[PDB]
Length: 318
Ligand SMILES: NC(=O)c1ccc[n+]([C@@H]2O[C@H](COP(=O)([O-])OP(=O)(O)OC[C@H]3O[C@@H](n4cnc5c(N)ncnc54)[C@H](OP(=O)(O)O)[C@@H]3O)[C@@H](O)[C@H]2O)c1
Ligand SMILES: O=c1[nH]oc2cccc(Nc3cc(C(F)(F)F)cc(C(F)(F)F)c3)c12
Ligand SMILES: [Cl-]
Image (tube, rainbow, N blue to C red; front, side, top):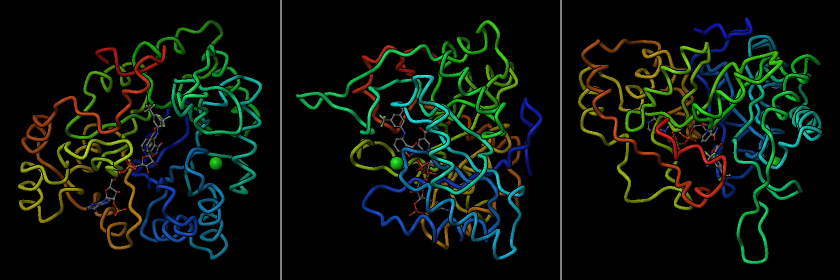
C-alpha cells in the first residue's frame, strides 16, 4: 500500500526506521535492513546523520542481487544534515550519500531539520565551552538546491523534516517555487498526534510521515527516562488485547487510518516480522477516537538545548 505524493511518485505507507545508536555495530544495519525487506518493508528511512548509509545501501543491493526485489520496488530515503544547508553544499551532500549507498538516486531526499549548524566535518560542531554552533541560512536557498537535485534525477522526490507550519509556509510561499515538499517527517504518536499540523499538511497536499511512532528508542542521552512509555499505555494495551495484536501494532495502525505514513524502527528480527502485520487488521472508528484521546503534547526528543535556535520548531502552537 502506497500514497500518491504531490509530484506523482508513490510512497509506501509503512517504512523501516534504520537509526541505531553508535554502540550498535555498523554491520547490524545491513543485517536488519535485509530482514526488513524480507518481511515486506519496501520503504527504508536513512540519513547522513545515521552513519549507516553504506550498510543500508548494501542491504538494498543484496535484495536486488538475490532477485527478491527490483530497485523500483524500494523507496529509499536519505536526509541532508544541518551542517550542509548552505546551497552549494546540498548537491555534494546528496552525491556523497549516493556514493555511500552505491545507489543512482534516492526516492526521497529531506532537509533533516530546519536548525542550521556550522558547516564542517562534525555532525554537532561545538565551541570552546561545548556549546553547539548554529548557522544562519535562508532555507529557501537550501530548498532551491534541493529542487535542482530533483531536476538532476538524483532524488525522485524532495521533502522536509521537523518543520512547523511557519517554516512550511516559508517554502510554500517562496517566489518561483518549483516543487512543494512532498512530505514533512515529524515526531508523531498517540501522545503527540500532531492533529493540527496534519490538517495543515493535508490542506497543502503534503504527506505527514511519523517518526518515533512507537514512542522512540528512549535513548537516555536525549529522552527523559521518567517520560511515560508509550507502549505501556493502558488504552493501547486494551486495544491490543481486543484485536489480538500488540501495542506497537495498534500505534502503527492508528497512523495508517488517519492518513499518516508511519516509520517503525526495530533491530530485532521477531519485531521486524511482527510490524508488517499492520496491514492484517483494522481499528474501528471508536478505537481511533480512544487513541485520539491519548494526545498530551509529549515530545520524547529533548530538544530544549536548541530552544534558542531561531528555527527551533517547537515554540509555535504547531
Ligand atoms: N527525521 C528525524 O529527525 C527523525 C527522528 C527520529 C527518528 N527518525 C526516523 O524514524 C525511525 C523510527 O523512529 P525511532 O527510531 O524513534 O523508533 P520507533 O520507531 O519509535 O521504535 C522505538 C522502539 O520500539 C521498539 N519496537 C519496534 N517494534 C516493536 C514491537 N513490535 N513491539 C515492541 N517494541 C517494538 C524498537 O526496539 P527494538 O529495536 O529492540 O525492536 C525501537 O527501538 C528512526 O529509526 C529514523 O529512521 C527520524
Ligand atoms: O533522525 C533521527 N533518527 O534517530 C534520531 C534520534 C535522535 C534525534 C534524531 N534527529 C534529530 C532531530 C532534531 C530535531 F527534531 F530537533 F530537529 C535534532 C537533532 C539534533 F541532534 F541535531 F539535535 C537530531 C534522530
Ligand atoms: Cl555519516
